[PDB]
Image (spheres, coloured by chain):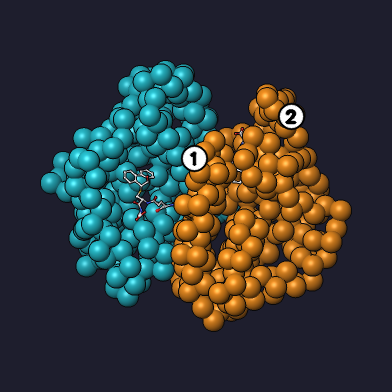
Chain colours: A cyan, B orange
Amino acid sequence: PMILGYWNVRGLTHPIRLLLEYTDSSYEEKRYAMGDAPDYDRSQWLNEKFKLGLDFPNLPYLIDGSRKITQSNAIMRYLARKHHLCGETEEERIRADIVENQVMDNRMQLIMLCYNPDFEKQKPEFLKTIPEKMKLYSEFLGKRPWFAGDKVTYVDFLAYDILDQYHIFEPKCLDAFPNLKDFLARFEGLKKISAYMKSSRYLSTPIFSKLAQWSNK
Amino acid sequence: PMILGYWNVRGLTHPIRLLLEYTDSSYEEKRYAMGDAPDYDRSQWLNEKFKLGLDFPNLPYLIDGSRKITQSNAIMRYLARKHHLCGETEEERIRADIVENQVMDNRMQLIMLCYNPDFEKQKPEFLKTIPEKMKLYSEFLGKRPWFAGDKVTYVDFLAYDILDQYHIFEPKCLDAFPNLKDFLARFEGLKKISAYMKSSRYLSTPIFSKLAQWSNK
Ligand SMILES: N[C@@H](CCC(=O)N[C@@H](CS[C@@H]1c2ccccc2-c2ccccc2[C@H]1O)C(=O)NCC(=O)O)C(=O)O
Ligand SMILES: N[C@@H](CCC(=O)N[C@@H](CS[C@@H]1c2ccccc2-c2ccccc2[C@H]1O)C(=O)NCC(=O)O)C(=O)O
């Protein structure tokens, strides 16, 4: 099968995993793992970083046959194209482009705070920043089944995961937004997702590496 | 006319600007201007932040009549799409997608350095990494005319931009890379581009904002 390479954690690859499962893809993984304190070895990835034929070597990577892909989003779009999970209208398309990109921004923000040396102090500030992010998501989604509109598409995977980690981080975070609440629920109800969540392949935590300041085991 | 909103610096919007020009889109701009130090007043933008009908208010933004778009890549594909500047085949789309995210990776690495108080102490280290990056681009492009292949697409705008910024950062960086130098001249030799760089609307620098440690002014 296809080979998904990434680190020993959730990080930014959950959407890929989920989607491979949703699509009935055949794949196996390679989960490199860093060593502990105090170096945090990377040797397992390093030794073959420039040995895999990847154009711009990085984690995660997807090896599908003769196709070698890097960049989380490109991976997502490749698999999206392979299975007809892209938006099919320009509106669906525009919505998807947007979600795709807002997701990473919100992701980068969570990540910045989780690696911040002064996590404790700047944070309650972050928490008060939440509601408003959620607010954007609720209103964008609206009355809609899925983020692009009437069709499940790959952004629904991106969306589900960040909404989840945000929710993981601030449990009440969704209380103000029902429809949001409903979406995870509806997402979790997709074909193979439920099985997958209960499976031995599921990797829900840690979201981050040891080093972190939050979500590190 | 469409309206392009962005700060009054190059930032990450250069690619849109080139594309609009290249596609001879009818448009107007609103280059919000930040105040100086020690406050960096952001009121020009802030005053209209939440009134533009934007899904997730941010900059840049593009308003094309009824349609409101945020997230640059989003912006670039929308326009790419109205003028057939997207990959046409599976191979093309994969290259374009990778490149799309890869530019954004190399981009943030730059800003990261450029807003780091410790900038002079970090440079030396950053400079080391540069050739390694150009090489990745030189090799990926190889003997293709365009980043995705035979035909120009919106990802060349993304590419020209980043490579140009790096070059600007370290003038010699494209020396070992004829491939690149040549891609740059070709890009810059495209009629509406040449034409635009000589226009009143051109804005090559500053690239970062006022609170940046490099290309701030
Ligand atoms: N833009 C790229 C991300 C590239 C990225 O930085 N890759 C990181 C892993 S994600 C990385 C990370 C590592 C551990 C734990 C968490 C994260 C993480 C989580 C979310 C978002 C981003 C990250 C990065 O810090 C990496 O280690 N790449 C290979 C290398 O540099 O040799 C993409 O979309 O794929
Ligand atoms: N992911 C979004 C970019 C979002 C981004 O951070 N926008 C910055 C503009 S780019 C941003 C930037 C700001 C000032 C000066 C330079 C830059 C810049 C330049 C190049 C690359 C990245 C940046 C960011 O700091 C911003 O001020 N958004 C509005 C807001 O926060 O309300 C996109 O790709 O469109």
Left or right of A112 in this view: B104: right
Say whether residue B201 is left or right of residue A18: right
Q: Chain ID for label 2?
A: B
Residue A177: x and y in percent read 43, 23
Label 1: state its secondary structure: helix
Q: Is residue A90 left or right of residue A197?
A: right
Residue wearing tag 2: B35
Which residue reaches farthest right?
A: B200
Task: State how far apart marks 1 and 2 are (Cα).
Answer: 24 Å
Q: Say which amino acid is labelled 1.
A: Asp
For disc 2, the neighbor class at 10 Å (few under 14, some 14 to 19, many from 20) is: some
Q: Which residue is mark 1?
A: A105
**Chain label for disc 1:** A
Q: Position of residue A123 (x, y in %)?
A: 41, 22
Beta carbon of the mark 1 residue lies under 8 A of ligand 2 = yes
* Residue under the point 72% across and 46% down: B206
The residue type indicated by label 2 comes to Gly
Q: Is residue B92 visible?
A: no
